[PDB]
Amino acid sequence: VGGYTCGANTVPYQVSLNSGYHFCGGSLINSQWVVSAAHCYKSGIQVRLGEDNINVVEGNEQFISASKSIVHPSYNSNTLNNDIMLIKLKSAASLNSRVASISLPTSCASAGTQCLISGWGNTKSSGTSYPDVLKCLKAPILSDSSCKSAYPGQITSNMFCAGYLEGGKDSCQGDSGGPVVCSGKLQGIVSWGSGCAQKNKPGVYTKVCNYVSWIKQTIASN
Image 1 (cartoon, helix red, strand yellow):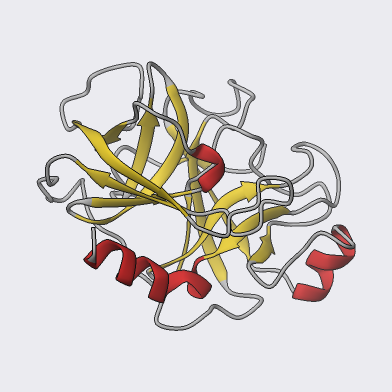
Image 2: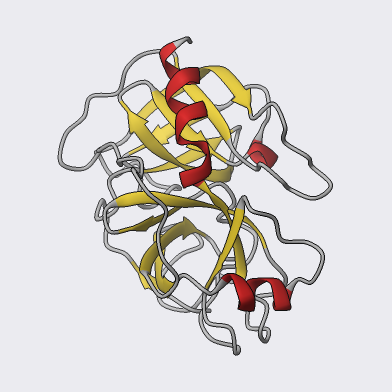
């Protein structure tokens, strides 16, 4: 599987994107904006903050609908290049201990840095808790060299790999759009990859540090 049960609200910037059901994660950036992957775009999104078990109302949730989605202008869905989107909330969230914003990088993270990847539902179900309670995995950023050698021809300047390569700990589709956080900065977004109790195919993440100027200009103008 990989990871473990996080504990409710221990990842306070984690959001669930719901359109009738949970279909993507994302990260709260400030009280009115969320970042997620552009392959998560859809009409009629609601943002669910303060969630642990997404099938039970536990008492700390905020359900706010999305008023505007902005997919990155150069997003390529064939190659998942520039796989990032911004979501504006109809109303601002009440920030508190369990619902918090995550900070944007001022610089890119080095390989070997340690990160926390978060999301619901790898696929599975029974490992420790629920495709319903939030799961966590700590993984090192991999070397550009290893990332590319795992996916020859497919990795761009806007992607990095993390995980363990050799049948270690990964995600599995479920977690798309969720955050990769390292040194208390949002450094990636769960994008794509190839297999979960598999073998040596690391996860592939959007490299948030390349988009900070777009994110701040876009959010300030919208």
